[PDB]
Image (cartoon, rainbow, N blue to C red):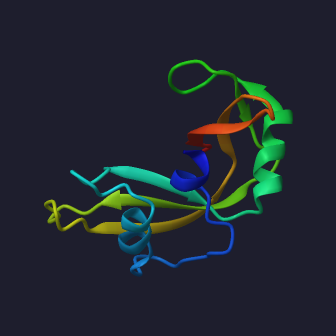
Amino acid sequence: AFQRQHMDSDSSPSSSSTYCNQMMRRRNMTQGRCKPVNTFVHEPLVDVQNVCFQEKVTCKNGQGNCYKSNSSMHITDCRLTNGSRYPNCAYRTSPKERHIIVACEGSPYVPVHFDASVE
């Protein structure tokens, strides 16, 4: 689910373009109801995966072993707009450069949950 919900390596959207409107639907987060908030990471998959071997930190939700990126990364926050009511799901697109925190699990040990962005 991490790849589908949070990875979009080849994109670099701008402030409240149609990006989030398009992506939240494309990545299956507007079915049944509009997912309120979500973040996409615009970095190569390999660099995001390497975060699992960087700075270990306490998670911002259930445990699961979280790690903070050594470097800030290019992300985009999607946030449901006020005048948005299902089935019509409208989002504000907010590009940012922040350190990210992910929960890693499995074998291979890779990111499985996006915990939060720093700052």
> How many numbered discs, if any?
0
Q: In the picture shown, does residue 77 fall above or below 49?
A: below
Residue at (63%, 21%) from the top-left corner?
A: 64
| Left or right for 45, reference 34 | right
Residue 68, by quadrant, is top right
Residue at (71%, 57%) from the top-left corner?
A: 73
**Which quarter of the image is occupied by the N terminus?**
top right
Image location of residue 8, percent across then percent down: 61, 65
Asked whether residue 54 is in view, the answer is no
**Which quarter of the image is occupied by the C terminus?**
top right
Asked whether residue 19 is in view, the answer is yes
Residue 58, by quadrant, is top right
Identify the residue at the far top of this view. Answer: 63
Residue at (47%, 66%) from the top-left corner?
A: 94
Image location of residue 88, percent across then percent down: 18, 68
The residue nearer to you, when weighing 106 against 35, is 106
Image location of residue 52, percent across then percent down: 79, 36
| Left or right for 54, reference 85 | right
Residue 104, by quadrant, is top right
Q: In the picture shown, does residue 22 fall above or below 97?
A: below
Residue at (76%, 50%) from the top-left corner?
A: 48
The residue nearer to you, when weighing 87 against 37, is 87
Identify the residue at the far front of this view. Answer: 107
Image location of residue 63, percent across then percent down: 59, 18
